[PDB]
Image (tube, rainbow, N blue to C red; front, side, top):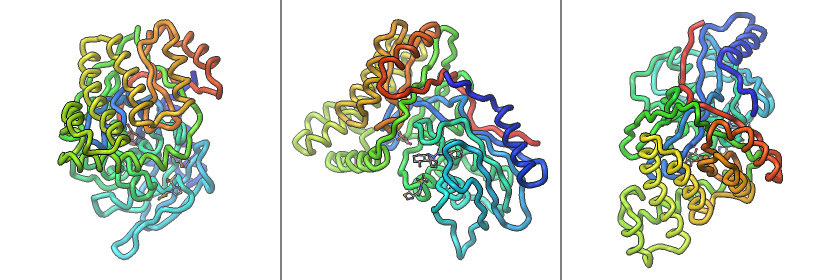
Length: 390
Ligand SMILES: O=C1CCCC2=C1C1(CCCCC1)N=C(Nc1nc3ccccc3o1)N2
Ligand SMILES: CS(=O)(=O)c1nccn1Cc1cscn1
Ligand SMILES: OC[C@H]1O[C@@H](O)[C@H](O)[C@@H](O)[C@H]1O
C-alpha cells in the first residue's frame, strides 16, 4: 500500500516550494481531502442518498494575499499538465476568467470566478496533492474545496457549507466541463475523522456515521485505467435519468419506487428502465447500508456493496472489465465483506471492506488476479477541509 503522506509533510513541501518561488514564507495554509464512496453510486444527482468518507489523501495549498489584484500559482503535483505555473488577474464585472491551459488551473479559476464574497484580493499560492490525479478519488474536488477554503481566509463568505459545495460544483461544471453531483465537494468540506457521511442529496441533511474499528479496514484499489467514457457517458446518464423522471411525472428518481417503476415500464425505454432501476435500488441499499453500519453489521454492509456493483454493472452499465475483475478477485479473499467500483465508473478505483488482518492477503491476490497494474490505498476515515495559520 502506497505510503500516504501526512498533512505536516505536504505542508512542509508546499512551504519550501513557496519560499523558493516567491521569496517569502507563506502566510496561510489549507487542506482538503479526496474521497471514497462506500455506497450510493450515481444517486447524488438523482437527489438520492450517498455514504462517502474523506480520505487521508489530500490537496494542500499554501499562500498569501497580494496587493495588485493578481493571482500567481505553482503546482508540484505529479500528473499536472504543463506549465506548472500560471498567472492571471482577478476577474472583474467586465471580464471573467475562462477555462484553458493548463487544465489544472481551471479548477482554481472556477472557484475564484464563482466565489460569492467581495472584495477578493489577488494572491500567490503553491498547490500540492497526494490524491492521484484523475484516479477516481476526487482530486479535483479536493483542489476546488482547498481553493474555496483558501479564499475564505482572504475574504470570509457568510453562507452555509452547501452553498460552498455548490460553488465548487459550479466550477467543475463550467470550468472543467464535468456536470458532477454534489457529493465529492460536500464530503471534502464536511468529512470527520472516524466517520462516514450520510448525505441526503434532496434535503441536504447530513449525518455523521461512526466507522472506526481496529478489526475493520477500507481497501482502495486503483485500476489505473480511465476509459474516455468516464467523461463522455457521465452526462448521458444524467439525461437518461432526467428523461425517466420526466415520463413518470416525478421531480426526481428519489420520488419513484421500484413498484411504481414496474407499473410504468411501457412508459420508458428498455435502457431507461434499467437506468432507473439501479438508482431506485441504490437509494434503498444506501439507507440499508447506513443502518447496517450503525449497528456494526459489516457482513450485511458488504453484501449490500456487492449488490451495488452488480447493479452498476448490469443496469446502469458504468463498470468495465478492469473494475469487474478487481471486484471478483476481491470477493475471493477470506475476510473480505464486500467490494464494488466506486466513483463515476469506466475505470478508477474499487472500494473493499475487509477485516484488517486480511488486507495483506487481499492485496497480493487482487494484484495477481489483475491483468493490469493495481495501486493500493489502506485508508481510515479522515477530516474535511482545514485551515492553519502560518
Ligand atoms: O484531465 C483530467 C480529467 C479527469 C479528472 C482529472 C483531470 C485532471 C486535469 C489535470 C491533470 C490530470 C487530471 N486532474 C483533475 N484533478 C486534479 N486535482 C488536483 C490537485 C492538485 C493539483 C492538480 C490537480 O488536478 N481531475
Ligand atoms: C481537465 S479539465 O476538464 O479541467 C479541461 N482540460 C482542458 C479543458 N478542460 C475543461 C474543459 C473541458 S470541457 C469544457 N471545459
Ligand atoms: O456516484 C457517482 C459520482 O460520480 C462522481 O464521479 C461524481 O463526481 C459524483 O458527483 C457522483 O455523481
